[PDB]
Amino acid sequence: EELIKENMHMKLYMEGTVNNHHFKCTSEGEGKPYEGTQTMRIKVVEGGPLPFAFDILATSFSRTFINHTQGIPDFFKQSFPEGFTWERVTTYEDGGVLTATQDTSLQDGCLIYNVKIRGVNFPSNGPVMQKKTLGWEANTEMLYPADGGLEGRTDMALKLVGGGHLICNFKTTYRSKKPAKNLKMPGVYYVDHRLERIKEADKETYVEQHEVAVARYCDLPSKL
Amino acid sequence: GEELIKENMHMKLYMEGTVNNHHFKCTSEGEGKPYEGTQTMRIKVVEGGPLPFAFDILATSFSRTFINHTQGIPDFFKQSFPEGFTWERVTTYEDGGVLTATQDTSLQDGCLIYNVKIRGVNFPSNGPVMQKKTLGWEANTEMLYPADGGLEGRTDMALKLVGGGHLICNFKTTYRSKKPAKNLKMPGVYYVDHRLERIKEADKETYVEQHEVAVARYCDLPSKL
Amino acid sequence: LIKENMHMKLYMEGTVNNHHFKCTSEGEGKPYEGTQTMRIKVVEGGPLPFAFDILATSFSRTFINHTQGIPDFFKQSFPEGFTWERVTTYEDGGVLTATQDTSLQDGCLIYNVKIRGVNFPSNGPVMQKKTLGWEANTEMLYPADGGLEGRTDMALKLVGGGHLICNFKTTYRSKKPAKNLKMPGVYYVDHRLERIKEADKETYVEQHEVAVARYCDLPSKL
Amino acid sequence: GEELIKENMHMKLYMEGTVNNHHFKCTSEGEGKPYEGTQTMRIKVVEGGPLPFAFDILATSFSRTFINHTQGIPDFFKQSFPEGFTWERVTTYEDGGVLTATQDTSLQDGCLIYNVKIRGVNFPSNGPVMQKKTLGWEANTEMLYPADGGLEGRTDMALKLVGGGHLICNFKTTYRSKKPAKNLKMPGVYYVDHRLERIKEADKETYVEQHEVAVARYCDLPSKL
């Protein structure tokens, strides 16, 4: 946890399939873990240009960079040096389903991400396959302890050309490679996220993304 | 329209429905401060009590006029008067239970009148809802966005269980105004932070008092665009 | 108790999205041959602003031909009768729940059904009335919790070709105690539900169903 | 197209992926009678064995060329050769497990070659899959229908459980031919009856032999139209 500095660098490898299209990506970036901000510069290195909106891959590119406010125990930062994993299913309301699994490790002071993606049943005439998307709205995730890890739930809204949205729901399981005796678990909490596309080029084979993420309790008054 | 909604408002409600195959009716009366986003409801199970399922699965079906819209967010619900509005929802529990609910909201002699219809099916007969192992809801954030001249809402809610766990459910809501579109200023995407709390119960949950605070906001995180 | 010929009467009420409605019907069929006809009237809320097809499956489990000696949970439930509850999820977001009570009063089968559908998209084929009835389907039934559960996918034909798929999950509960019921194991019902006649923007509808229960007759290595 | 698929065919397969963060690899070989709908596959877990999860969840990912198409139903799979075809699938278990799979089917020197990738998530640790308390699959009927120059399939499958009862799952499949649509005669709606059986196993499911029979038909029920 004192392994995680005020500025940290990251590198990533990603591969998988969406429908029948194979691809690979790599990225590099940096952020301030305690401030909850980060930047990633991404290259589609195989299978580009993608025949699907890049927005569906956006959330798969970094949990160490969440500002855990209010003394909330930090499952992610606490996991180092052992590191951690995550597994997710994202279900779009028009049929697309994307699962993703991820390994996070720390090697010579650099965070190293290895991601796998498997997307299926995206409608060939819907807005993902037809590239009619304009990035994600901000969202709140709820995290709660479950099976010795953390589970997360959120709904995210994918902006469409013309002003509408396509909604998706995701369910994540976060697992620490640190033995449970050395981790103090949080209770229920919330993470507010704003994931933004900063730059793109060459039919989204180059993308720059930024994320700000701040964890908190619910601050509403309680009658109890 | 907004002028019809005063600083202090009373409510009256009728509910009937089924869960699994158990029929029930409820009645309630309450009061709140619509602009401050707080309300209290005192609820009676008048038929089919004691219910064989956790009253918690009905708790979110008992009041959208009572949201504090911060930051100038246009208020779809308050703007709807005097015509009023309706809502429809499906709540899906991760162990199989599915609860649909439809609701009519009207203003009648300065009283808010709720008529609610519930149909819940396929709760597991040996799960925590049917065996009454629940302890109320965690706080939650709902996302609301415009769709089809109305609003839709999405949230995930966590139902606390005896022993420390949670059972998660997801709900998808459509809110429809009875006011003609040309007379509504529509909001964009926004968020509502909610805390629904049970304050009293008696007689195997045939008498229940609930309180809700709801506060609407934009996302306050800084943006790079 | 359940004779070779049987008549039926039904009341239905409910809501889809925000549209309230009521229907009634009568028909007859042959419970042992798995066939039945129902003539159906929309008596309040007509004409419906949604495709009647979404209601078709809610209008009769006593009329399934249970072959090969499969213990027939439905027919054994008399005179006490039985209920069912269902959720149908459409792949474009419509969700319809339905609960039903089936009783036998003075030789006639009596049905009381309640419908609540939500979230049907206003541009989709259901709310546009651009559907052309159901394909045939096979339902899987299996014992669970002292009742039976059913699983099927159904394909709703669309004006202009293609289909909209839905999935349903059904729970069938007997009003007769467990100890006076022989339970089946896993089995399958083949169904063909067709519309014979409509009139007056679907406010009158005639429907026929044939339903036959069977085991799987593929050969087994075990 | 169909001329390349003989009365007897051989298959080889490679599989890899992950279920709840356990990585694994499998190989298989086998043979069958494509036009009679029968086939046998002998499978080795070559990396990650013994698996911490019921092998039953992988069984449906190990061969669409082996469907007996009765009644003149145009056979999308056999017509796709020599180019071959792919499939993609999501299987949703009623206790939360989700398994996505994608497959490449090709024909090389008269051998069918299968390349399969598997990604399973959220299988509950005290459920039957992760506790390895399953006893194979019931028979099932799949519905197939054309959609967008492809074929989609829908089915519910019942997984037999140690102690009696079943865990139910649903799957949604998309089959895509590599052959241009120009050269394919598409079927309409039809049905496939399946019976997938475990014939033998050894060494804690690191060796498994499976058989499948699959027969396509229309519905034989009389029609009133």
Image (cartoon, coloured by chain):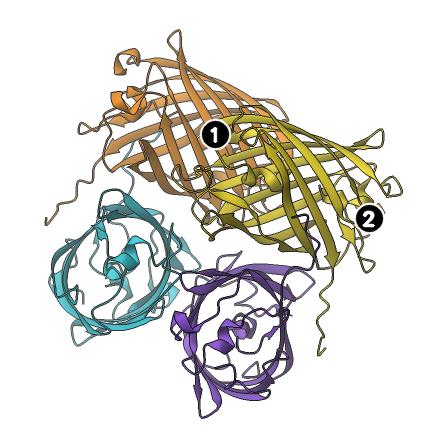
Chain colours: A yellow, B purple, C cyan, D orange
Mark 1 belongs to which subunit?
A: D
Q: In the shown orientation, is residue D27 left or right of residue B82?
A: right
Q: Residue at x 25, y 59 (%)?
A: C51
Q: Residue at x 36, y 21 (%)?
A: D178
Q: Are marks 1 and 2 in contact (CB under 8 Å)?
A: no
Residue annotated with mark 2: A34
- Whether residue C176 appears in this view of the structure is yes
* In the depicted structure, whether residue B35 falls above or below residue A135: below
Tell me the tag on residue A30.
Answer: none
Residue C25 screen position, x and y as percent: 17, 70
Q: Secondary structure at mark 1?
A: strand
Tell me the amino acid under the disc marked 1. Thr
Per the model, the C-alpha gap separating discs 1 and 2 is: 39 Å
Residue B132 screen position, x and y as percent: 57, 70
Residue that protrudes farthest toward the right in the picture? A2
Residue D102 screen position, x and y as percent: 47, 29
Residue B199 image-quadrant placement:
bottom right
- Between A57 and D27, which is closer to the camera in this rendering? A57
The residue mark sitting in front, 1 or 2, is 2
**Mark 1 Cα within 10 Å, few/some/many (few <14, many 20+)?**
many
* In the depicted structure, whether residue C59 falls above or below residue B117: above
* In the depicted structure, whether residue B218 falls above or below residue D71: below
Residue annotated with mark 1: D102
Q: In the shown orientation, is residue B71 left or right of residue A123?
A: right
| Whether marks 1 and 2 lie on the same chain | no
Q: Residue at x 71, y 41 (%)?
A: A62
Residue D55 screen position, x and y as percent: 53, 33
**Mark 2 Cα within 10 Å, few/some/many (few <14, many 20+)?**
some
- Whether residue A147 appears in this view of the structure is no
Q: Residue at x 28, y 15 (%)?
A: D1
Tell me the amino acid under the disc marked 2. Tyr
Residue B127 image-quadrant placement:
bottom right
